[PDB]
Image 1 (cartoon, rainbow, N blue to C red):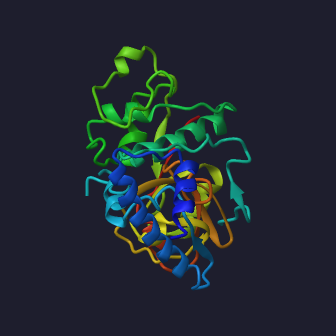
Image 2: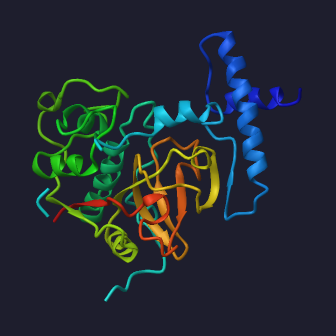
Length: 292
């Protein structure tokens, strides 16, 4: 019927083009079915809405397993902050990156905080290598998940290279670190936010983008167009992101699904539900870089 004129202009909009002629038909049947969900959910009147982003393309299971499950995996050991924080305005957030079908988000999450903290310490905003952390961190399982701390603690001890030195390939390989000469930057340590504490997390955002984790495999998450996300997500976190800010109702989240998802790649997640886990279990495991 109708919808074909839309689907066409939607592929068109997201530089999607398909393998067979038969996928374009599967993709459509999916598209149309995600459209129904979208449209039937944006009648519930909540603080956020779904929309046809880069994942209307995809059934939820498809989506589930190519874009979530970046963590893990599965050691040792007077709050008064701004009303709002958006680190992007202070010039310390690089443009959104697309992680692709790779569960690299643990690496992405880590770099988007390292990239930040050096500008928060050096004045100077660069883009470093996810691919490196990907290839080289031996504690992580590569494109099938990893550990933000592991990454952050690799840069603290070893360091990291510029994006265009060790560029992203969306596929794990050899550790070509030693082949790219001197590290581009190196951080001085890692800290952890007191988990299941919001004010703790808020506070640590106040100073520097924190690397947090959440349950990203909900259907409402994949089709998230905009608004303040309030659920329903659970708690079985499975995706690593960087909280580059907040405001009195939300925590501002930067994501790795490119600028075609969410609010241009961001998602403001509802905050202060007295839920200790934080919405989507956001408070369960949060870390930030240190630099002097």
